[PDB]
Image (spheres, coloured by chain):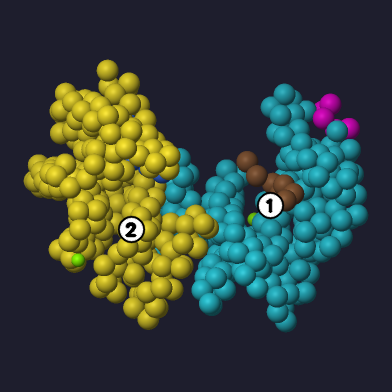
Chain colours: A blue, B yellow, C cyan, D brown
């Protein structure tokens, strides 16, 4: 559910 | 399989594969480039990361679909197919970790390159931890923790609080705390302190660096909103 | 590689792979199911088609990206990588055509199954024609034409004008006319006549069949709008 | 550019 790094 | 191709051609082809959204090709080209034995530039490190993040990302999304079907069900087909995808994912993580160990990390002298590779190491142990269930699962979690921790220690000593790789590392270490280590308070504290210290350093940045840093700060804020 | 798995397990796993958006897996499972030697059900034919359409669709999209880069450029890397993707695409088309020839088409007695497989045969020769440039290119185009034509002749004799496979076949044969055979007037006439004759047969349909038929009629109308 | 059959 949470955001990890992504472009 | 890439030993007979020039390094520069492998890099060129990795960029073409990215444009074609052929990420398995991209990862194989970048693996071949790493195996040439020369250190990677800033742009080349990015290409390596994007390639494998896309490959494992597809495997993780498939594993989560199958895992939920398997949980809803609990013949052997759903479990068998989840295990197949899981083995393939573990193989990709092992390949990346092998590139980092042989010999990207030991040859990475600058803070920017060393933090980048230690963040990758933490991420791929984190992906292994997401599917882990056996004797080594606590050791897998601690391997992720240890890689992230070393990267954090270097980034805090050597980089400004707005540096994109420092921000991305803190973001992913906070996800590790929340999702893997069952430490939501640590996750929240890390995300808050990272956001606040970056906010206070934005005034030093050009417009282009400002755009890079605030983009990642927004991901930290998105998680804080989800978690609080 | 699928000879040791039960047919029903291959089918089950193909459905799981579709849900996981693992279309290469899906295609391999359905190839294994075909190679069991039994005829395919309506639902199973669908699974086979969806799997390979997704696989080749990704290859076609990548080939088009690389082809445009190559055209804009005209060292060897863009051409070399386009040729690699092109060879991989040709291999997948050859695999599908091989399944149709050995022995799906010859065992397909009913109009629904035979038209389905001849439409597939036309489509995969069409995909071969999209990348073809050599001695066999006219023969590839005529192989697509001949497969589509036989499917059309059967569909017109044996199916109502609203039948989804009849509609989809006419749609794709019209794309063949426009894009491959350089016959835009034939493409437009086929699309119009197909649309109009389906319109006049909608009154015979249930609400669910009506939904299926009008969905494909809208694609015919989209093309007519693009072409006129 | 034109649409062939798709789900
Ligand atoms: Mg060095
Ligand atoms: Mg039969």
Marks 2 and 1 sit apart, C-alpha to C-alpha, by 51 Å
Q: Is residue B212 magenta?
A: no
Asked whether, in this view, residue C28 is left or right of residue B125, the answer is: right
Residue B121's mark? none
The reply to whether label 2 and label 1 mark residues of one chain is no
* Mark 2 or 1: the one toward you: 2
Q: Which quadrant is home to the N terminus of chain B?
A: bottom left
Chain of the residue under label 1: C
* Stretch in magenta: C200-204
Chain of the residue under label 2: B
Asked whether, in this view, residue B39 is left or right of residue B77, the answer is: left
The residue closer to the viewer here, C3 or C67, is C67
Q: Report the predominant secondary structure element of the magenta stretch.
A: helix
Q: Where is residue B226 drawn, in percent x and y?
A: 32, 22
Residue B42's mark? 2
Give neighbour class at mark 1: few <14, some 14-19, many 20+ (Cα, 10 Å).
many
The residue closer to the viewer here, C158 or B36, is B36
Residue under the point 62% across and 60% down = C64
Asked whether, in this view, residue B159 is left or right of residue C102, the answer is: left
Residue under the point 28% across and 49% down = B86
Q: Quadrant of residue C143?
A: bottom right
Q: Quadrant of residue C86?
A: bottom right
Disc 1 Cβ-to-ligand 2 distance below 8 Å:
no
Residue under the point 84% across and 48% down = C227
Q: Which residue is mark 1?
A: C116
Q: Are marks 2 and 1 in contact (CB under 8 Å)?
A: no
């Amino acid at each position: 559910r949470p955001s990890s790094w992504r472009q | 399989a890439m030993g007979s191709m020039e390094r520069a051609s492998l890099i060129q082809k990795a960029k073409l594969a990215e444009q074609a959204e052929r990420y398995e090709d991209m990862a194989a080209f970048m693996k071949g480039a790493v195996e040439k034995g020369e250190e990677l530039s800033c742009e080349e490190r990015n290409l390596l990361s994007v390639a494998y993040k896309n490959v494992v990302g597809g495997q993780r999304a498939a594993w989560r679909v199958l895992s939920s079907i398997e949980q809803k069900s609990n013949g052997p087909e759903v479990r068998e197919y989840r295990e197949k995808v899981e083995t393939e994912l573990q193989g990709v993580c092992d390949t990346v970790l092998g590139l980092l160990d042989s010999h990207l990390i030991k040859e990475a002298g600058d803070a920017e390159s060393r933090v980048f590779y230690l963040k990758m190491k933490g991420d791929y142990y984190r992906y292994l931890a997401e599917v882990a269930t056996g004797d080594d699962k606590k050791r897998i979690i601690d391997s992720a923790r240890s890689a992230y921790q070393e990267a954090m220690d270097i980034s805090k000593k050597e980089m400004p609080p707005t540096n994109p790789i420092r921000l991305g590392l803190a973001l992913n270490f906070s996800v590790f705390h929340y999702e893997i280590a069952n430490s939501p308070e640590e996750a929240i504290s890390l995300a808050k302190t990272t956001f606040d210290e970056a906010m206070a350093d934005l005034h030093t940045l050009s417009e282009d660096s400002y755009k890079d840093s605030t983009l990642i700060m927004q991901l930290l804020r998105d998680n804080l909103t989800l978690w609080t």
